[PDB]
Amino acid sequence: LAASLACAL
Ligand SMILES: [Pb+2]
């Protein structure tokens, strides 16, 4: 989940 947020942004 954490990585998905950073990736998206
Ligand atoms: Pb990525």
Image (spheres, grey):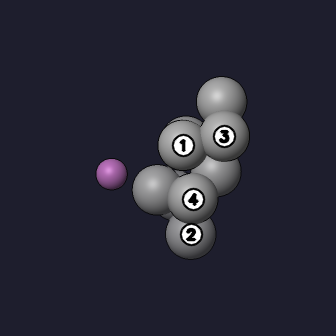
**Distance between the alpha carbons at the discs numbered 1 and 4:** 5 Å
Q: Which residue is mark 1?
A: 3
**Distance between the alpha carbons at the discs numbered 3 and 1:** 4 Å
**Distance between the alpha carbons at the discs numbered 2 and 1:** 10 Å
Instruction: Give the side of residue 1 with respect to residue 6, left or right.
Output: right
Disc 4 element: helix
Query: CB of mark 4 within 8 Å of CB of mark 3?
Result: yes
Type of amino acid at the residue the image marks with label 1? Ala
Report x, y in % for residue 2: 66, 40
Query: CB of mark 1 within 8 Å of CB of mark 4?
Result: yes
Q: Which residue is mark 4?
A: 6
**Distance between the alpha carbons at the discs numbered 4 and 3:** 7 Å
Type of amino acid at the residue the image marks with label 4? Ala
The local crowd at label 2, few if under 14, some if 14 to 19, many if 20 or more residues have their Cα within 10 Å, is few
Question: Mark 4: is the Cβ under 8 angstroms from ligand 1?
Answer: yes
Relative to 9, is 6 above or below? above
Question: If the image is split into quadrants, where does the N terminus sit?
Answer: top right
Mark toward the viewer: 4 or 2: 4
